[PDB]
Image (cartoon, coloured by chain):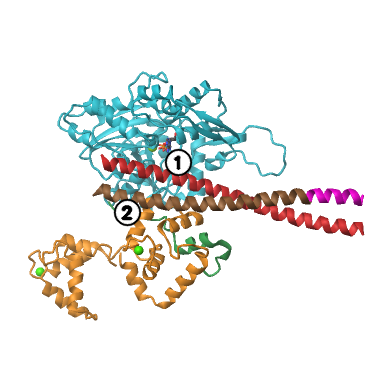
Chain colours: A red, B cyan, C green, D orange, E brown
């Protein structure tokens, strides 16, 4: 009985760990995309303010 | 067929087919051999990672640029860089494509001759042509006059041109550029406790310089403000944590451009070598050069330089002339865009150095009529 | 001065780069 | 310009349904119901193409007339067929210049619109006088009532 | 042996579940900030285009 319980717990542990690792990898990719979005936002903001100042002059 | 507009540069190699808007592949020009021993067997470890691959494994490499100041100091590494550029970043064999390299003004002859000899013997191109890096930047602006200050990463040169007639006696080439600013920033960061020494950490200091530094409109007022308030201290996260805070190092690093006495150089800043380059020109084309001052090159991307330079020149120049500084948003790739435009012209199609011509006169053909 | 565009690669390649695994018909 | 409109008007509802379903599948999960300039630019970045935000604004201004920044059904099809430019090089400059110089049969440097009328009679496509009027308006930039050589270059610029 | 295996399996399942929930939260917040940043980028690009046209005029 104990052997059966241990094997079932082992299988559940392995599958849940695999799914967690894959979702973690995708989360890392999402963070990379967020960083790129941050950079794009900052660059565009600088563009806009510079152009507005030049237009005023 | 289409022409290959390569642009060696010093710090970033920019290449792409003629007739487009932006270079196809842009990657640092560094070749880094591994320096540690290596214990895993069969890992497939190469002997030299070039280009953008060595900016990801830079933790265990010793990166070394093959181009010091415009000139090329290590020909084997430069050949390796060119081979990578042709075969892996563009995937076009050079046997079927003309090439258009670019070269700084006032460079040693042997560099140019060796460049053409390599392109004709090793890669075996059909025809190659070498052009001065400033005329292209003037092409890209769509002008035909103007004095262009092309402050790259290796060398800053200032070529004045009028009505298409270049003035060879008024070229002022100065060897302060982005690399010296990186070294000076790395040297003044030590005043807060952060020590970067390894050739890999020079890349981190370069990233700090790109993302944080800016050119002050007035230097003394900024030095006084940064010493009282704390509204300037911007923080930055290293590749491992331990954020750092840059104080008045922000505008002191790029200030070296206007006061080269900071790094011990004697010469005058980029604000005064432009005025000197203008004053060497004839008395009747000075107004046009004043009105069409062009900026190019990577290092002229600092936030707030197009105003500091205009203020300085307006201080130097006579009060009546109008001073205008052209700073297109596509500054970094201006030279390559101009190169694409020049290679796409029909009138230019007979200026290439054809291979049979090289076979008849040797590598010294480049100094001849085919310039 | 004319302009030439090559970054606009053939639309099939763009569709492939967009889709990937689901690039079966488009 | 309206070149993609012409190309897709040659096409039929097959392309309409095709691009509709393509929007359904790829733009799945979107909140706007159309394609935006920033939307398509980010899509290009995701696939691997590197367009610039200034280019994004330029292209959307080219495709969007109402100022919405998105694509109407006809505008959506025009933009979708726009990203690839199959046809280029627009006929030949010198041959068409000769054709236009001989078009001025009076050889006065000016184009009589009656010559245009006769040439169109030769063309014979289903067209009303107002259609050629609009075409001349597209061509007669200075509104001189004739076809200027430079304006002849302009209106035939890139025309296959 | 079975007792020790069961204890280790229980501890592993606990830690994997905790890491999985952390990953789900990180994915959610990353997606939220990503969408907000993309919308801000669209706004900035539109403003830049408009002001550039006005500047040319
Ligand atoms: N956005 C930026 N802000 C400040 N400095 C920059 C920026 N981009 C590049 N640089 C500096 O310019 C250099 C790249 O110059 P580049 O024009 O590529 O030289 P080259 O003429 O050899 O191509 C980099 O080393 C960097 O120090
Ligand atoms: Ca619209
Ligand atoms: Ca006529
Ligand atoms: Mg350069």
Q: Residue furthest front?
A: B229
In the picture shown, does residue B124 fall above or below B108?
below
Residue depicted at 45% across the width and 53% down the height:
E39
Relative to residue B304, is residue B275 drawn left or right?
A: left
The chain to which mark 2 is attached is C
The main secondary structure of the magenta stretch is: helix
Quarter residue B276 falls in: top left
Marks 1 & 2, CB-CB < 8 Å contact: no
Chain letter of disc 1 in the image: B
Mark identifier at residue A8: none
What's drawn in magenta, residue-wise?
A: E1-12
**Label annotation for residue B13:** 1
**Looking at the picture, how far across and down is residue B288, in whole percent?**
19, 36
Q: Residue at x 78, y 54 (%)?
A: A13
Q: Nearer the viewer, residue A40 or E27?
A: E27
Q: Secondary structure at mark 1?
A: strand
Q: Nearer the viewer, residue D87 or B72?
A: D87
In magenta stretch: residue E13: no
- Residue E29 place in picture, x, y as percent: 58, 50
Residue at 89 percent across and 59 percent down: it is A4
- Determine if residue B364 is in view: yes
Q: Which residue is mark 2?
A: C3
């Amino acid at each position: 009985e104990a052997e059966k319980a241990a094997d079932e717990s082992e299988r559940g542990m392995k599958v849940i760990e695999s799914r967690a690792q894959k979702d973690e990898e995708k989360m890392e990719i999402q963070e990379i995309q967020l960083k790129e979005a941050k950079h794009i936002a900052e660059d565009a903001d600088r563009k806009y303010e510079e152009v507005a100042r030049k237009l005023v002059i | 067929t289409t022409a290959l507009v390569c642009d060696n540069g010093s710090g970033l190699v920019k290449a792409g087919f003629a007739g487009d808007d932006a270079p196809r592949a842009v990657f640092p020009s560094i070749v880094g051999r591994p320096r540690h021993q290596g214990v895993m067997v069969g890992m497939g470890q190469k002997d030299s990672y070039v280009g953008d691959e060595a900016q990801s494994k830079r933790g265990i490499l010793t990166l070394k640029y093959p181009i010091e100041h415009g000139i090329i100091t290590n020909w084997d590494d430069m050949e390796k860089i060119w081979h990578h550029t042709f075969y892996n970043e563009l995937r076009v064999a050079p046997e079927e494509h003309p090439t258009l390299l670019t070269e700084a003004p006032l460079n040693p002859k042997a560099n140019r001759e060796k460049m053409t000899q390599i392109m004709f013997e090793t890669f075996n191109v059909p025809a190659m042509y070498v052009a001065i890096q400033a005329v292209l930047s003037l092409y890209a602006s769509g002008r035909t006059t103007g004095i262009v200050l092309d402050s790259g990463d290796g060398v800053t040169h200032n070529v004045p041109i009028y009505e298409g007639y270049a003035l060879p006696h008024a070229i002022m080439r100065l060897d302060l550029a982005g690399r010296d600013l990186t070294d000076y920033l790395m040297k003044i960061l030590t005043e807060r406790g952060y020590s970067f020494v390894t050739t890999a950490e020079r890349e981190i200091v370069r990233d700090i310089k790109e993302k944080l530094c800016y050119v002050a409109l007035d230097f003394e007022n900024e030095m006084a403000t940064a010493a009282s308030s704390s509204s300037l201290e911007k923080s930055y996260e290293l590749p491992d944590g331990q954020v750092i805070t840059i104080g008045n190092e922000r505008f002191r690093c790029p200030e070296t451009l206007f006061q080269p006495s900071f790094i011990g150089m004697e010469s005058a800043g980029i604000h005064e070598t432009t005025y000197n380059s203008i004053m060497k020109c004839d008395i009747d084309i000075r107004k046009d050069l004043y009105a069409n001052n062009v900026l190019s090159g990577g290092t002229t991307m600092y936030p707030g330089i197009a105003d500091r330079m205009q203020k300085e020149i307006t201080a130097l120049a006579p009060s009546t002339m109008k001073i205008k500084i052209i700073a297109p948003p596509e500054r970094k790739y201006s030279v390559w865009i101009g190169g694409s435009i020049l290679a796409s012209l029909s009138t230019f199609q007979q200026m290439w150095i054809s291979k049979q011509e090289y076979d008849e006169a040797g590598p010294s053909i480049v100094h001849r009529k085919c310039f | 001065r004319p302009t030439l565009r090559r970054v606009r690669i053939s639309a099939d390649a763009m569709m492939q780069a967009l889709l990937g695994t689901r690039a079966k018909e488009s | 310009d309206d070149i993609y409109k012409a190309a897709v008007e040659q096409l039929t509802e097959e392309q309409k349904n095709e691009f509709k379903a393509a929007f359904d599948i790829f733009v799945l999960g979107a909140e706007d119901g159309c394609i935006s300039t920033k939307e398509l630019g980010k899509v290009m970045r995701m696939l691997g193409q590197n367009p610039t935000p200034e280019e994004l604004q330029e292209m959307i201004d080219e495709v969007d007339e109402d100022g919405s920044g998105t694509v109407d059904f006809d505008e959506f099809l025009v933009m979708m067929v726009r990203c690839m430019k199959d046809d280029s090089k627009g006929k030949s400059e010198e041959e068409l210049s000769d054709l236009f110089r001989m078009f001025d049969k009076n050889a006065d440097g000016y184009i009589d619109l009656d010559e245009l009328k006769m040439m169109l009679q030769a063309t014979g496509e289903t067209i009303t006088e107002d259609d050629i009027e609009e075409l001349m308006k597209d061509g007669d930039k200075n509104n001189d009532g004739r076809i200027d050589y430079d304006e002849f270059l302009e209106f035939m610029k890139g025309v296959e």
